[PDB]
Amino acid sequence: DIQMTQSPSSLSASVGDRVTVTCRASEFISRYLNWYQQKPGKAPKVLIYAASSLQSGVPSRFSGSGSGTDFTLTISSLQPEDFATYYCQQSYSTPYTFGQGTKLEIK
Amino acid sequence: EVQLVESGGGLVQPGGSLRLSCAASGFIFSNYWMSWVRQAPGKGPEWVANIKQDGSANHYVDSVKGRFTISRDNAKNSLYLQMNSLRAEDTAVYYCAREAYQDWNYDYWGQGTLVTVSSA
Amino acid sequence: DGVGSSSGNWHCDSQWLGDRVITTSTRTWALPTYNNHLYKQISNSTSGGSSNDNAYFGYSTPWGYFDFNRFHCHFSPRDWQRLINNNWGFRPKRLNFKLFNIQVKEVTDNNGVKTIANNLTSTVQVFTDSDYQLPYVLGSAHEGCLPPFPADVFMIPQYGYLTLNDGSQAVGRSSFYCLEYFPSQMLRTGNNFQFSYEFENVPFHSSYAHSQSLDRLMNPLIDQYLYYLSKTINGSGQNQQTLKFSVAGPSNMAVQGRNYIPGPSYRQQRVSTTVTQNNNSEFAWPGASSWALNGRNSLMNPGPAMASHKEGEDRFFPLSGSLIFGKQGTGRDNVDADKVMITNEEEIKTTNPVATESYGQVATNHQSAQAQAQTGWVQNQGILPGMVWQDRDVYLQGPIWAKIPHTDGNFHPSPLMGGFGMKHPPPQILIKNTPVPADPPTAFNKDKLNSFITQYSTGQVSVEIEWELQKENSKRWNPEIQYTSNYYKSNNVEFAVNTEGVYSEPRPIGTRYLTRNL
Amino acid sequence: FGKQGTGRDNVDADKVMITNEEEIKTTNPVATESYGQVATNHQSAQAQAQTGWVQNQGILPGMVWQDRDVYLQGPIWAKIPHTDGNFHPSPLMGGFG
Amino acid sequence: EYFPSQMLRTGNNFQFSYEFENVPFHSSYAHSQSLDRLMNPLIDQYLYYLSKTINGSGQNQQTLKFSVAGPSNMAVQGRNYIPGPSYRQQRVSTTVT
Amino acid sequence: QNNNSEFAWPGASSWALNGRNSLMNPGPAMASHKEGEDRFFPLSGSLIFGKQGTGRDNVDADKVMITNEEEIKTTNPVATESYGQVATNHQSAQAQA
Amino acid sequence: KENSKRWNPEIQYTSNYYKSNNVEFAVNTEGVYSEPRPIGTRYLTRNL
Amino acid sequence: DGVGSSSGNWHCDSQWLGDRVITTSTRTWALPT
Amino acid sequence: LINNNWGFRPKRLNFKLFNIQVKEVTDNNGVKTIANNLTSTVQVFTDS
Amino acid sequence: KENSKRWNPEIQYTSNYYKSNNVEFAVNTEGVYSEPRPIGTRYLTRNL
Amino acid sequence: YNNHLYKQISNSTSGGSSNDNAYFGYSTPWGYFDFNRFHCHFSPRDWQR
Amino acid sequence: DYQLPYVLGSAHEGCLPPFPADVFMIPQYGYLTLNDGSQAVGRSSFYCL
């Protein structure tokens, strides 16, 4: 299957900071890559899907870019609500695979 | 609007069999692919199985092949996961998700049910 | 007529008469029961992003069909040689089809041992789709055609079609077709079937190569009376701008004025058969030229007709710009390069741009005292007034005709995999075994009968095509290139059977040997 | 098209009727999408394969297409301009050239 | 005024007749197939395409692998006809947000 | 008004055939210049005749006669201008057209 | 045949464009033909 | 006529001609005792 | 029919019965064989 | 004329039965004729 | 129309914006008949039919 | 029969002079065939007039 590698495993920043998360794919998965934000005790919530496109009802500070094997999740003007675990998932082929996850910390 | 509810979660001894049911009230249930996703405690979530919107086809992750059966009833708008020969590794929170049309991401997720496999 | 009389004879040969050649092929076929006499809805079973381009919806039918649409169906290798060495062009004229010596067999399997017997009262149904009312599957380069070698017995392929789909689901605009809802002729073992067909007028395939190139049409001894701009500066320095003009002549043939330009291009990625020269990455799908239709991406294959490679470089081929045939016995998936035969379109370099090159350069701005002249590469170029081009060549293994889609408009409808485009191509010929139910219950039941006698049929097919020829008139003094066999000793004769009785075709054979002036 | 009683200037979207050419998706590219991709270079041991988006594509041999549909409110005919050449003179707002 | 014209008082009438020149029938129908779906979904092609350019991860993994185009992958099959020309339009949504 | 560099050959529109580059001359029929600007001409887009007694090589501009296709501006694009503009993306709440 | 002078368009029997897992009045994946709904004869109108 | 000859063909279709429509159906049957 | 017409009615009827096959079933020890019986007949009449 | 062999029924252009304050493609109470929506020509289907 | 007069007409605007909108022509005293829309010739029921 | 390479469509010199009193020299005929660089190929044609 395809392996998804997410970097960095953990990150800490402050409100207003710019945060960037990188996801790498073992095989070409085209634009079918999703970013999910998850908070304890809740299901993962999709932020960005299909590489660049943003989910409706999600703040414009979340952005996504990349295609083929390399993708990046960008957060501008960080907020207290933003601190969570972030996953990159590939919906290109079965079995669908998720990234290890990036945890964000208050500073 | 779109609601997914998971039921049948609970503790069972290893080798035990459990059945999970997903209820969907918010959309046309027969137009969408449905998946089962589990998240082990302290781990990232993991894809278990999906089934076709008419139920003609289905896919399973290798670890669970032969021990799980995904099933779909379109008239009752319910998704069923059948678990047999349960293991300690299998215990996780099970999530029922709907795969987005065209994009294929999980637009909607159920609250989920915790399922525990314990020796005791 | 009768059980003990034969309803047809075996006709295989070619008749070369003047400007006409008539080929006749006879084969033996076997027809099974498909889908247990059922129509069945089918769709792609995959999920995810990858499925998107591969999504489909359609139906498989109990019917089979006859496909003679490859050239090696109608021509022996010697006849194909006799054609391509002596003629500048050819095209089909008439078609005659026969189906005869029908045998229906029943199979009773008991305790792992199967018995086969004649069922003399069973029928086989056949009809042609003369009104082009069914979806037309014969122009998709499919398997299941009559075998090139006359002694081989072949299985008849199952008919199926696709209709409109959204993902794997259908839409209200999607069509369903019952083939039982056509009138068809029913045949017991004494009956036979035939029909004749008339090809609509098509241009001669151009089975020749140009002995001139589009850019070399001038008289090499004479100047033009046209001028071109030779110098924009007197030399190095400031404020050296000038306009100088020269005559275009034998010394510089690149700047001469020309009346005609090469044809359209859609660039292909270039792949080498020397693998160390290729990039160390997977770029087969990702680096491929494609077109999108309703959200789905289709590979551009083979695409517009373009020269496969530049002169002197034969190790390169377009990524999906050529027709690739398998050698005999080649597997289905992930075979090596020596297992396949990559054809090339090197003959058409005279009028057509190279597949892996840009078409040319255009100006991207206005040069000025403050701005240098800028150019850009033209990666794809559509039709321009003054373009001339050649179509793709046809091969002994390749297709003959295609059906032109029924549309408001088309341009140069010649099909891109090669051959003759036709609004009314040779019709589809559908065949199935009539179901014979097993013994029903003795009390009435309204359900349809799902229990049948296992049964199959076999018989003979002959197809006859008249071909019109266009003879070579050339005044060329020196001898031509010809297609020929090689005298060197080998363990096998090419285009023959081996010691196990397997017929193979050593290499793909194109049509273009004789030359014509451009 | 405008609905009955629709003003001349800066009307809202519910005041107009936007027709669509969704029927011709079978043979025609989507208006808002690229036609496809082409190779922009030669891949080599030192260079990865590169593609680019085709934003506009003129006629190629082997293309088939549908014309625009006609409407009850729409035009019937157009006059083909008198010129040395034209291609597929069918008028672009629909109808018979 | 420099054309000849007929003058009509209240009792006069005017008429003329006109003959349309031959035009193609407007195609008032939609296609139940798509240009990319014309193949028989049950059968393979005898054509091959390039499936793999590398054996796997590593250095110097270049290879050429070829597969048959078939029902499993309909996107890579050889086709005789391609969709028509395009000139890209910008895409606007009726949902203004 | 021209740039101080040699751009005659380097800045010329061309087409390639079997590896060889040919100047595009005169090329497709296009209007030589916009209205009001007659001092400009296409680099190799016009027919250029010599005056009587003009030498063969590197003659000045007053020794030749540059014809123009200004009459065809009504239907044809100007030779030195772009044809037009196309959309290169999908505009969205996060992306300008 | 219908001779009517009605100006506005009639009610017609028609298929629905919305996507479905099956085409109505066709076979399913197991080859079973079904008739989705009963279809009457009365669509066109006449004056009383 | 004979064992090895067919005594009829398969006719299914509709013909719409003016004010007349002609339907033809062919089916395969099984008759028990 | 129903979209384009104000009325309809049947006129002529034509009926055919053909390609008759008579099968005999010999069942021995739980396994049944089916064969053609070429000399058997089927009776048909219409109640005119 | 349409020659098709399609088994299932076509999409047709039709009026909607639901009650409304006005008949579509008619006058209103002030005598104003309107055209509710644009109507295209493409309903019947053909094989590609 | 035009009090029986032919009159020369041209765009009244100035500036860069006018460029694409520039025109020159004539208005005439004459009128003309235009039946070139389909709803001229078809009722909604005929168009359906 | 258009069997020779056709050089008349290349805008060459050697045409009849525009002014009728001028005496003109007849140009020499020549043609090009397929070439790889300055070398020929087996597909190249030679014509004896």
Image (tube, coloured by chain):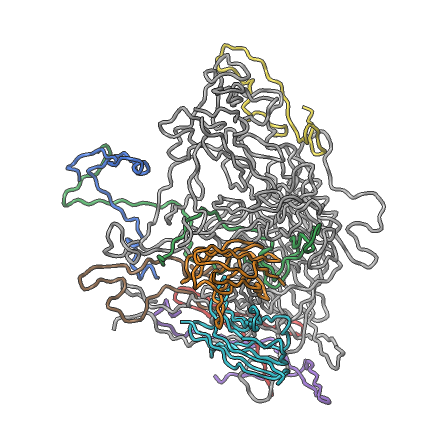
Chain colours: A orange, B cyan, E green, H red, I purple, J brown, K blue, L yellow
Query: Would you say residue C314 is visible in this rendering?
Result: yes
Task: Residue at 22%, 37% (x, y): give it.
Answer: K27
Question: Which residue corresponds to the image point at 49% horizontal and 65% vertical from the top-left?
Answer: A84
- Compared with L18, A25 (above or below) is below
| The quadrant where residue J31 appears | bottom left
Q: Decide which of K41, E76 is in the foreground and name it.
A: E76
On the image, the x and y values in percent for residue C85 come to 71, 40
Quarter holding the N terminus of chain A is bottom right
Q: C200 or C80: which is nearer to us?
A: C80
Q: Judge left or right: residue A9 versus residue C512.
A: left
Residue F37 locus on image (x, y percent): 38, 27
In the image, is residue C434 above or below residue C398? below
Q: Residue B4 vs residue B58: left or right?
A: left
Tally of numbered tags: 0
Q: Position of residue D13 (x, y in %)?
A: 31, 56
Residue F11 placed where, x, y %? 52, 30
L1 to C412, vertically: above or below: above
